[PDB]
Length: 103
Ligand SMILES: [Zn+2]
Image (cartoon, rainbow, N blue to C red; front, side, top):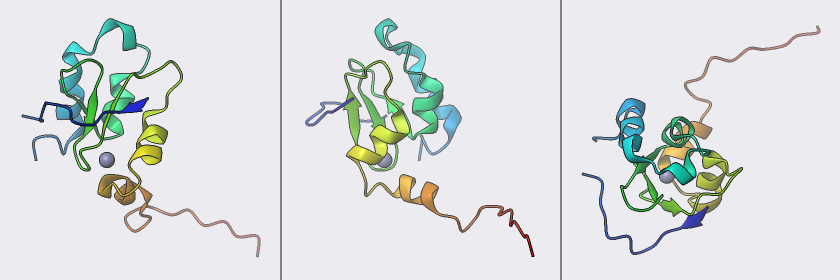
């Protein structure tokens, strides 16, 4: 995917939840049906309605020209490393931990 700058659209707290983000993809175009809206939205992205351009609900990063085989989370991390949503996902503070012992 490619970073989009100077995109002349804005997202009309609305997109904090997965369901709202997924719903944005009602008009996701035919030529990108292979990059799942379900993965895109999980990865924080909202469809802007312009081309195949999606925008992160948290960092405002925009990506378009999605290509076969692109991983939305990896594209997110590569392009927008200071995103607070990604950093929250990298946090191990709130997560259930399984501990191995061979003692
Ligand atoms: Zn982001």
